[PDB]
Image (tube, helix red, strand yellow):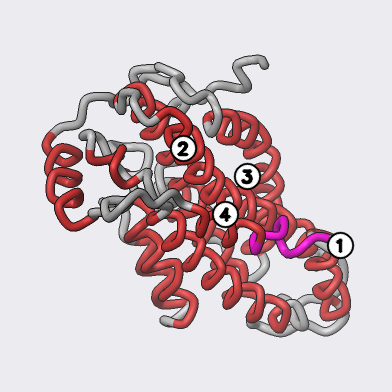
Amino acid sequence: KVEQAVETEPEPELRQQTEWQSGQRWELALGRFWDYLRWVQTLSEQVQEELLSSQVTQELRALMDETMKELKAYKSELEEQLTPVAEETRARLSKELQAAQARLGADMEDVCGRLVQYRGEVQAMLGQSTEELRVRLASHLRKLRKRLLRDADDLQKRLAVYQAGAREGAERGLSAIRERLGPLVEQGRVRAATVGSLAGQPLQERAQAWGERLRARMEEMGSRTRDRLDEVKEQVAEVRAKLEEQAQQIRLQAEAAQARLKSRFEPLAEDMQRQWAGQVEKVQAAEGTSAAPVPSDNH
């Protein structure tokens, strides 16, 4: 909201590389998703009015399945072929996707949860503050929106290379998607989320009122905002997700980094270069300006 996800603003290389590679089909979903993704940001009491109905959730879950439907579709067909090698290196292509894969569902599923929780919590009270919940809503959404972002690219980047064409690896490719998810549904029955988002909680005719809400919404939010992660766990519900997630994130970015290194080393050797200072931020000394990325905060 200020640097966690704002660092990408000045770094259009992510939107340029994806728009050039993908084209528009996949870039569309992930493109429109980022719009409402950050739009969810709030501050003024207006947030309590929007919480009435799962608006950002319906729009988020709507696009989430879109980018995931187009990516998974083109992916399965992409796995059929790998880089121009087919010998041993291809073995890393199986694990590589495993990382970017778990990263997709992780953030995605985390999205619907952030809303379903934030809404299910406030809707249970209907008479609390907003900042107390915003403090965590800023960082949580910051890392949730940042990950899904830096991931969408780092993931689509590998799909651009696979377009090359392999021989033996062609068999291992199909295995990659099989090593990620099998019994489950892509990530974790995301469909089940589309149902909850519909739940909402209408009153009489103000369950949304986004019309006037959006007015002060962006006004106060952009005005200056009074939170900037002041470390104040109010809901302590959604924070758990980003907390336990941010921890495992290291396992993903790690396998995805070590693999990508050699993965792109075959086709080229400049990716790590532009990515060294053009990926998104590279986590400039820890995360969060104030409210550091809590590991778990116990239970």
Bounds of the magenta segment: 184-191
- Disc 3 marks a residue whose amino acid type is Gln
Q: Residue at image x 60%, y 35%? A: 241
Q: Which of the two labelled residues, at mark 4 and mark 1, occupies the earlier sequence position?
A: 1
Asked if residue 28 is among those painted magenta in the image, a careful observer would answer: no
| Residue drawn at 71 percent across, 83 percent down | 77
What type is the residue that disc 1 sits on? Answer: Pro
Q: Comparing marks 2 and 3, which lies closer to the viewer? A: 2
Q: How much space separates mark 4 and mark 1, taking CA atoms?
A: 22 Å
Q: Nearer the viewer, residue 20 or 266?
A: 20
Dot placed on the residue nearer the N-terminal end, 3 or 1: 1
Q: Which mark is residue 118?
A: 2
Given contact means CB atoms under 8 Å apart, are the residues at marks 4 and 1 in contact?
no
Choose top left, top right, bottom left or bottom right for residue 56: bottom left
Between the C-alphas of marks 4 and 2, the distance is 13 Å
Query: Left or right: 293 with respect to 205?
Result: right
Q: In the rendering, at what x and y percent does residue 151 appear?
A: 54, 55
Q: What amino acid type is highlighted by mark number 4?
A: Gly
First in sequence: mark 2 vs mark 3: 2
Q: Which mark is residue 253?
A: 3
Question: Could you tell me residue 115's position as x and y percent?
Answer: 47, 45
Q: Which quadrant of the rendered structure holds the C terminus?
A: top right
Image quarter of residue 173:
bottom right
Residue neighbourhood size for the residue with mark 4, other residues' Cα within 10 Å, grouped as few (<14), some (14–19), many (≥20): some
Q: Which mark is residue 196?
A: 4
Disc nearer the start of the sequence (2/1):
2
Which residue: 40% across, 42% down?
A: 281
| Residue at mark 3 to residue at mark 1: CA–CA distance | 24 Å
Q: Residues within 10 Å of mark 1 (few under 14, many from 20)?
A: few
Residue at disc 4, secondary structure = helix
Residue 183 in which image quadrant: bottom right
